[PDB]
Amino acid sequence: TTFVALYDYESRTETDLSFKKGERLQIVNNTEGDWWLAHSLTTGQTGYIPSNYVAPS
Amino acid sequence: TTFVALYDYESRTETDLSFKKGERLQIVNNTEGDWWLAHSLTTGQTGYIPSNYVAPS
């Protein structure tokens, strides 16, 4: 339930969290679900999606 | 391996993918892992993190 960072991470956008190796993090349950990097076979566009918006074929 | 969108999603940043209900999506394996919304107990900051950078307490 409480995780520890193994590496530094520097934020690349306004929505991600920067953290330093050793920081203690708690995951936030939320309605979007985990986010996955995805590719649209319909549009050819690519980027992150909220997993709770999709289902398997 | 191939997912279907259950809902429209409109992109909120430059890194997320917009898609319409019914679109067909493939997930992209990558080194960051799934992303989780997280809260830093060290800094009080909050936002998304790459899951493969952390481990359980």
Image (tube, coloured by chain):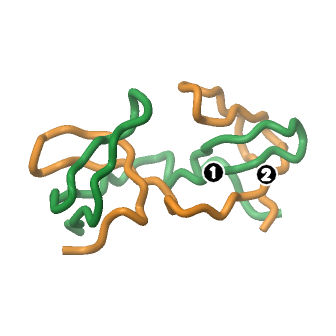
Chain colours: A green, B orange
Q: Residue at x 23, y 57 (%)?
A: A26
Q: Amino acid at mark 2?
A: Leu
- Tag 1 subunit: A
Q: Dividing the image into 4 quarters, which one contains the C terminus of chain B?
A: bottom left
Residue at the far left in the pictured view: B42
Residue for point 21% across, 59% down: A21
In-image side of A17 versus A33 (left or right):
left
Residue A18 position, x and y percent, is: 28, 42
Residue A31 appears at what percent x and percent y? 46, 47
Q: Secondary structure at mark 2?
A: strand
Q: Do residues under tags 1 and 2 come within 8 Å of each other at their CB atoms?
A: no
Which dot, 1 or 2, sits closer to the camera? 1
Point 54% across, 26% down: residue? B13
The residue identified by callout 2 is B25
Tell me the kind of residue under disc 1. Leu
Instruction: Indicate whether A34 appears above or below B45.
Output: below
